[PDB]
Length: 285
Length: 49
Length: 63
Image (cartoon, rainbow over all chains, first blue to last red; front, top):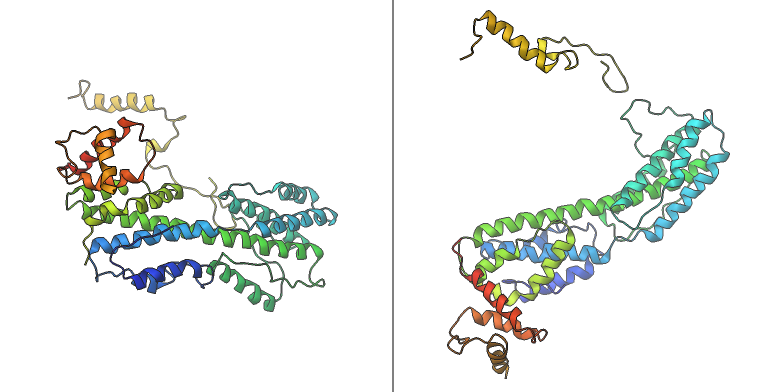
């Protein structure tokens, strides 16, 4: 929330407040993606205790900025259920040369549903697609995997190369900024392949999209939690060198595990509450 | 025994060099210990040091 | 005015003897400024005693 700092000039503290409003807009949403913000830390210019503590207000607040804006695929996630229902409807009418091998894949395609839990949102998309991509190759009688341990990669089936560059470029922009994504890229022709593949490629695009939004989240969120754990243990090595009430007081603040965000989210609201008492421990000016 | 080279289930063969490679259902652990005394008795070490 | 609120904690709440003045204990000054902000639970005389007690252990530990 209301982050507070030590040796930063007021002109720089206002710039960090500007980072919150611009976070949805700026390309490449990562603190590592904006090196100049890391150069606002004032490292070497100030004492090493300030150099480590100054980042701790950012990484705790940058993690707060991620939780508040929140991933929100639910407006698109319901559309994923519709296209999965459309493949389920058109998947029965289509003839097969071995219906028993294919019908079992259709049953798993029907069972897929999203729970309220966010950690399961990625895994549910994968099984819903693997049952379809194995099915989509059968429509063109394409060769499919037989060896055990060789699950088929998720990929588009039979599409023009000009269509590929326009749609794959969007996936690179999903990792660039998961906060604002729309399924505007749709241009499948009725002439291509079959009505199944048109239902599938629209599903595979949303299916990769739910993962590319989710994988861009957890891979960064795991990193920001890892960064705080490194800065804290390095901070303890320096605070231990001096013994004082405020100095030992800071060591108790770092005893809480950074693992799981709520354990760290309480740490940020706590540290703001007691800024006045331990501030003397850090040299300044 | 078969293995899993890529896109294949090729057969594999490997000698069992030492006598201890045998399965416990064919080479019981009590068997190896009582068998061990046969050589110490051949070494005349019935009372081991 | 604000100084008078600290006397309510030292007397009515903590029941600290006047020989243990707030000026007499330099590290106490950092703590009472925070307790004054918490208007709640003035009725519980004991909770402030155990809290002021444990914080002295934070001040005094070579280990």
